[PDB]
Length: 538
Ligand code: SRM
Ligand code: SF4
Ligand SMILES: [Cl-]
Ligand SMILES: [Cl-]
Ligand SMILES: [K+]
Image 1: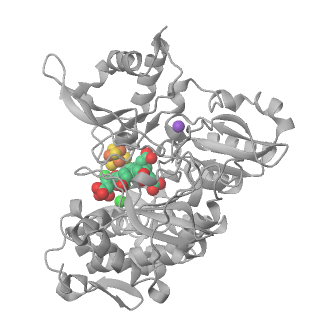
Image 2: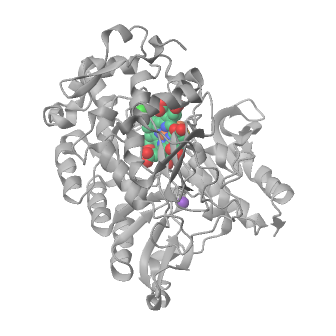
Image 3: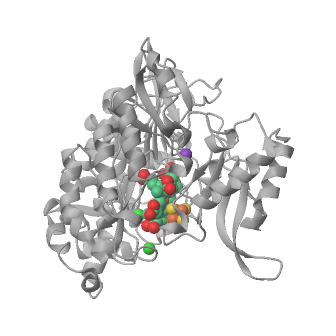
């Protein structure tokens, strides 16, 4: 690779970072949008105030403002549901480590409550909140209300650093390696400029996923993140080995690979900045399917990429990876659903199943009430779109288990429901080929009626090849497709994936059977469970 390839392609201009004029040839349309107007101005120069006052019908009549609502608003966490819910916006937060409060939960519920049938909320596969039904005129007030309860929505979509994922058992688990909350909190604060906005990292070639590991279980899925911090001692010091470039896409899925780098714990933010700077500065900005960070690593090679990170470290040192990390390979992923003792004596946490991550405002108020009456006001989200309420005096558990709402959000659902994960699908997502959430519930219920099992089989349903519900990590994955019934009529289908493994011995699953009509999935899945996962016909 030439020395010329290493020339930074972006420059700071008026507090923002923009593509240098020599590197603007052949860029994709999204890069054009970013050049035409810096998205961060909608927040940092309060451009949202004036945009929000324009009727949508009129917004749609010019390119600049249509690009504002359909693309630039994703820098403010706002996603126009143009096809399936015209004029309404899904809104996505930053929620490092999945940690929320009862007050935050009540505030979000109060927002969606206003929108009635157009509102609801969802836990995401990055242990994050999404809310729905938002109208543009309400945006200025919602942004103020979020700030008031200590939330931000900044930089949560498009070409930005996504929600920092950590250990859902951080601080409470007797077996944790290192509490991940301080580090995911620092990362989020760094990425969003302490909720003011951070333009140094808001103009990447593409989305970029971080996680910090603190569990032997690897609840954080480090193998599928752009940057994963793996806890490791080096020369007597606590820190992290770094894995880089994991990603899923319609074209390619790849697991993260060692950068061959270790940082002390205090260097978590400096190396996150160095890697993002290298990615921002040097990454390809053509075909969107070749813009993820792994593609840069493949072009430069891991050593060439590593050198770029190294020059962007303070004092310009990057130590080599330590031989062995702290994650024990001898480990069985623990079920966190149900009631479990904390490391603080006399306290328990409870894991509650949220069916396919979907909640309404009344449900959110109930969960917030439980967290206040039984816990410490804290609610934790998980990447299986479930919840944990920590910090419950164990003497209160008898009473808690009698709460009516626990019959809906159960601490002990059937085993197949425990592991069930589903993306938004075509109820709201315009890219979706099929309906996912209702369908996956109905199918899973009918399957579980027919078989009993002991192994915790994880089933993931995703509505299109973007694979937001990560079908490549599942024991059985279902990817939306259109197919044909026996009479040649169009019907919703799934491509069925097998082979996905998580934890230290991770593996990416692959298509096993294409184009299965959804209405035929029950018998197929019953047989797979009996033949491959030890299930027993009832
Ligand atoms: C909500 C969520 C799925 C869920 O039900 O849980 C989601 C939903 C969306 N994803 Fe995703 N993705 C979500 C996690 C994922 C993950 C899983 C992960 O992060 O571990 C992946 C695969 C992992 C990865 O990216 O490496 C992912 C892969 C993407 C892709 C393909 C990325 C690529 O490189 O090609 C897109 C399309 C794109 O960015 O070009 C997509 C884009 C979309 C959009 C924004 C599509 C569009 O705008 O309509 C979806 C919004 C639908 C809606 O209204 O909810 N989403 N998305 C997740 C929100 C996570 C969060 O809180 O930040
Ligand atoms: S996998 Fe496809 S259908 Fe599901 S939320 Fe992602 S983009 Fe939408
Ligand atoms: Cl996006
Ligand atoms: Cl859409
Ligand atoms: K769930």
